[PDB]
Image 1 (cartoon, protein in one colour):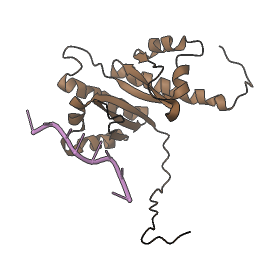
Image 2 (tube, chains in turn blue, green):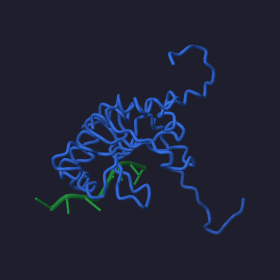
Image 3 (tube, chains in turn cyan, brown):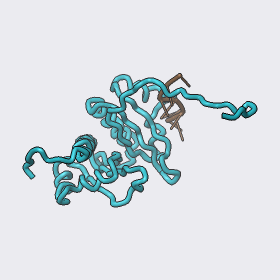
Image 4 (spheres, chains in turn orange, red):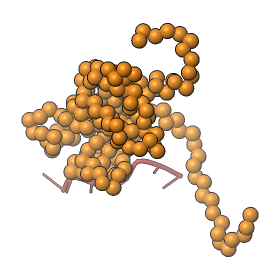
Length: 191
RNA sequence: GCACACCC
């Protein structure tokens, strides 16, 4: 080594084994609403984390050009139901999406870069039928974010019921897509 | 009166 005058450092406070196998997605709410979504000193938003039993966080602008702040929901689908159900209700609170309109709030879910291409389907038919099952608007971009992050986003537009069902289904195929690592069809499939 | 927090 080399003894540098007061040039000694380290600081390694990264302990504990917290299993991050909870579903974590980014809920798209523009800066015009995100503020009041947190609510009063940010107390009841953390209270929400308690009664939902999930990790409710507000993501700082992932891009400096964002007019929106995404809610980082880390929780089981049981909790996500309340969390996102009430988050869409916060849209209703100020009626940003539309006064008479039913809730139309975008949710952004992070999928592996190639997995977004495969949610379209191995034949390309799957993305169309996904919309038919999810009851939501699933738009899969060819760009979104460079594969430098090996991960992109699909945008879900519609009602929270639809969004919640869409999110979990696309997030669900991700695991099955990654199963390609096995590489070896030691069995059949009806496809 | 509406926002800020979310970990050590």
